Image (cartoon, rainbow, N blue to C red; front, side):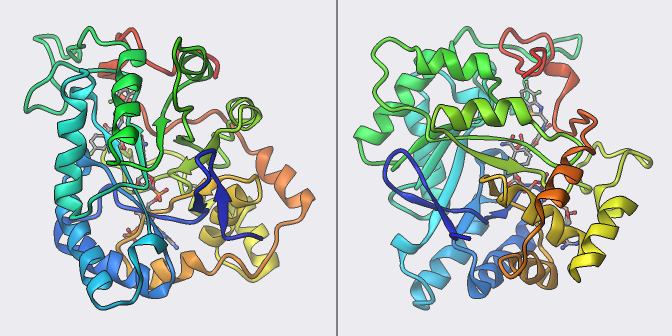
Length: 316
Ligand SMILES: NC(=O)c1ccc[n+]([C@@H]2O[C@H](COP(=O)([O-])OP(=O)(O)OC[C@H]3O[C@@H](n4cnc5c(N)ncnc54)[C@H](OP(=O)(O)O)[C@@H]3O)[C@@H](O)[C@H]2O)c1
Ligand SMILES: O=C(O)COc1cc(F)ccc1C(=O)NCc1nc2c(F)c(F)cc(F)c2s1
């Protein structure tokens, strides 16, 4: 199948990317260098991951070594919640460009629909543990993001963790200039997202699946939470194809026409994760994998459930 998907801005986005959340600063530079050597051309980053400078070192080294040209790379970053205010959006984007050492981003996403009080703290909490919200609304933040496209700082803009009603709010924004090109959401066999994906694709918005392997290294992961990598049913499907369960879990979203960004700092896994273009899951395999859905969401935070723009109270 095609290695890249067409965005509404006319650009092509590689369907397979390397995730960087939780990749240690002292290991992420080597991880990205190896990824590029192996063929990855799409890297997913975020200022909140606190490792963008190190990711940038890897990109610059490979550009300098002439292993790849800038136009061949698709770099993605995200605007954190404490910079939703109209006047802080550009500076937040410039800081990321500075750390990544690039003069433009291929895609810039609003990380979460929730705006937090501005400050040095990523999660400002009040005396009772509730996140302190800012009185900014998604529409004004979108307007500020559109300005980055007109100024040449980013080629395309998108959203992440937005439910269908929040996507609709943007699509119905008065004066809408640029439609969101991508909605990056959690997606794996235990959280299939059929409704939201169908909705987004029907609107011409590309969906990127994050935490495709269940994010086993998430910090809040608890000793006996479900494990996709060890699900016997998924292991059986992998065995039948002579592939690993990770390769099956990565191939799964690809056949649903989604972009997938698995994370790894391990050279062997980085290479194994890229060898998913040589096999195909049957329609039967796909429908079976979809039947494992349990609406089990791993990426959410209790401290944000009171925010007016919390995205997961809606069914989708
Ligand atoms: N927009 C958002 O709100 C948002 C939220 C969550 C995630 N994301 C993005 O999505 C990316 C991926 O999601 P994620 O980091 O949550 O988790 P993930 O990719 O589902 O899982 C990462 C874990 O799987 C392991 N792994 C990788 N390949 C493996 C393989 N072939 N075999 C066995 N284990 C393997 C990794 O180990 P090693 O690293 O030790 O190899 C790591 O512990 C992120 O890094 C980030 O870029 C975005
Ligand atoms: O965010 C990432 O890329 C990966 O995750 C994280 C990555 C980091 F570098 C720091 C924290 C998280 C985290 O705690 N993640 C869970 C969230 N859930 C919510 C939530 F439900 C909201 F309504 C608003 C919000 F902002 C968050 S953050």
